[PDB]
Length: 459
Ligand SMILES: Cc1cccc(C(=O)N(C)C)c1C
Ligand SMILES: [Zn+2]
Ligand SMILES: [Zn+2]
Ligand SMILES: [Zn+2]
Image (tube, rainbow, N blue to C red):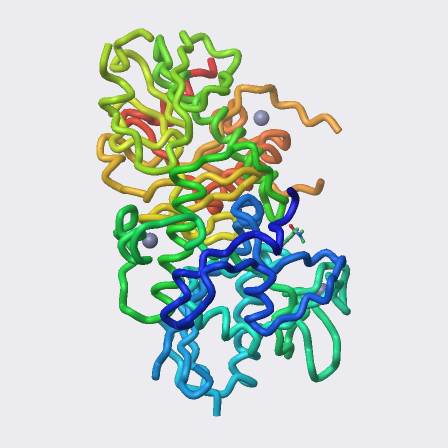
């Protein structure tokens, strides 16, 4: 059971208004044939245009919602909407474009999917809430066949050119007119009562319905993301590396060790309450402090209510010492806390748009993160940048310019001039810090945190 069998049954009830008289008994094989495509018993890596919900989840970076509305059916114009917010109008003769023939519309479709997906995926997955016109319009911009490679590189082919008779990936498709071997999945097959809007609005209040096709394409993908990542969480699915994943993760660990280590030296808390990931380790292994752990998985729907984590009878007194919420998203953090919170609004190849203000962060694993909320940090302040090091001034073993900085908290800086070793390490730490902030993470600390208290930890 690797791929979706073409002999699987397709429920056609959702198609009978755009297609009256459609047989209740239908398979993917007959559906594809009816869409105008011929699969000629092909054993060439493209067994079916439609994929399983499990194959869709592994390829979430490829998801593009797609909906077609009737403006007036070969005689009338179609409005093509995509989850990118783009609406094109095809004539058979919320960015809204006027009516144009299919030969120019298909050129724009290749450009849009290529620029949207080149740094996300090796393919496209059209996420549908199928009513009929979107399947019957696919023959005008899609060509299928055996799996292929790009003419300019080794990636798989996602586009085709009728001008040159060649194939290309999303990076080399400039001037290409057809979508080659796309994938698709009908959300309506998953068994739902009622229309798209009623089901979307039960969980999401951020995407409204301006009745245009892109609005429905957006609600469709949002509902698919909710069903696969909000209410169903699977942290056993690995995702390919497509960016700075390894640098971001390493940076996050360095920043965590640094920030926690300095808070324990500056304020000398007797106990630390580590609230979060049940697999967590002490980030500052050699610290003096009484380290106590509390398990809480990454919340994917709503942020944890602090009353349900801390109350209902552990030291019991979370008000003693400091609380560490490293990626443990709560509605309101206590005043005595150190916090790392992912900002869902961040623009990046790792952060995909999500459900109800949330976002889908895909870094080795997929984590739907709830909406960023500035009100959760009322009792805290933003943690400013600083580099602390109590290690010795010793070079050992890269060209140099002297470092002058008020945030290089070291004996060498205290004593007048920063040494080469702490200048190299300071600059590296600032690069890891910038990587982490730019990736979307935000740091917050208790109001009494002051780096001035770190100078007396050198005598
Ligand atoms: C953009 C990017 C970068 C590196 C690897 C991939 C990938 O997963 N492929 C299977 C090609 C992608 C899509
Ligand atoms: Zn290529
Ligand atoms: Zn939504
Ligand atoms: Zn030094």
